[PDB]
Amino acid sequence: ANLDIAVYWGQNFDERSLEATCDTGNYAYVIIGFLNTFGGGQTPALDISGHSPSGLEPQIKHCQSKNVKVLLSIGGPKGPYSLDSRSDANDLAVYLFNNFLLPPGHSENRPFGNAVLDGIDFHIEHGGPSQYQLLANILSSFRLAGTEFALTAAPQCVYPDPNLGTVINSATFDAIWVQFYNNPQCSYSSGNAEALMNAWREWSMKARTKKVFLGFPAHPDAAGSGYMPPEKVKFHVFPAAKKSYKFGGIMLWDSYWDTVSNFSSKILGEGW
């Protein structure tokens, strides 16, 4: 196989630290979640489950020294986020660029201190497209001006995605991790992977991106539905997903649960 695994981090105060997560050697991408407050008159705020944002500065740098890419995810499963006006989109693009994607500008301040992140993940779970296209257009423009970073997306598994479908059609995302969970119409169920295989086929053929990753829960308690044991993922999904030029790897929801289940350890042949 030789497998890239992306994992979400930041969902529990008590979880394995960001640096220990990177030291497992199991992950190519660590996505910090979430910037879940923005738009509609609010100042942006993070909800990273009580972790100290400034305390993450050195852990992010340590991750990066080990060649792990670290992204910040916007939106998330819950939160008062919206982007209904063009002014909201512009404000949020400029805020992310200055505070996360560029070096230090030495006087107004930065959540993560002097860390510089490797990209932005769109985990937009409600709202409609709304202005997310304009947000992506502006971030993409920044990328073309010298700041080299990734733009990724985490749509639900029904194609096209109601919140990000149109933005995914612009081809602006470097990679997408589809959530094959919490929807029985497109995820694993009953030992009936048919729904899952049919959705994967659609996504891998139609999504305008270079890399599509399959997102799975790391433990049965991690999602309402869609948990698929690692032996079945390896036997059932890999042989088919590997005939795709767009196959990127898998994404796991999430670090806290993967620590408990050792799902990534099993999928790889012990991950040291």
Image: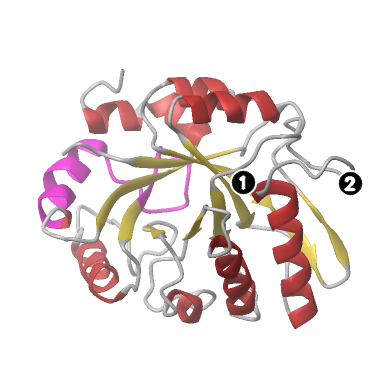
Q: Which residues are magenta?
A: 215-240
Quadrant of the rendered structure where residue 156 is?
Answer: bottom left
**Amino acid type indicated by mark 1:** Gly
N-terminal of the two: label 2 or label 1? Answer: 1
Q: Residues within 10 Å of mark 1 (few under 14, many from 20)?
A: many
Q: Is residue 123 left or right of residue 183?
A: right
- Helix, strand or loop status at disc 2: loop
Q: Is residue 250 left or right of residue 77?
A: left
- Label 1 sits on residue: 33
Residue occupying image coordinates x 84% and y 40%: 106
Can you see residue 36?
A: no
User: Which x, y percent locates residue 75?
Assistant: 65, 59
The residue sitting at 68% across, 47% down in the picture is 100
| Residue at the extreme front | 146
* Residue 152 located within the stretch drawn in magenta: no
Residue 82 lies in quadrant: bottom right
Residue that carries the numbered disc 2 in the rendered image: 108
**Residue 51 pos. (x, y %):** 72, 31
Looking at the rendered structure, the secondary structure element under dot 1 is strand
**Label 2: few (<14), some or many (≥20) within 10 Å?**
few
Q: Is residue 157 visible?
A: yes
Q: Nearer the viewer, residue 5 or 67?
A: 67
Q: Quadrant of the N terminus?
A: top left
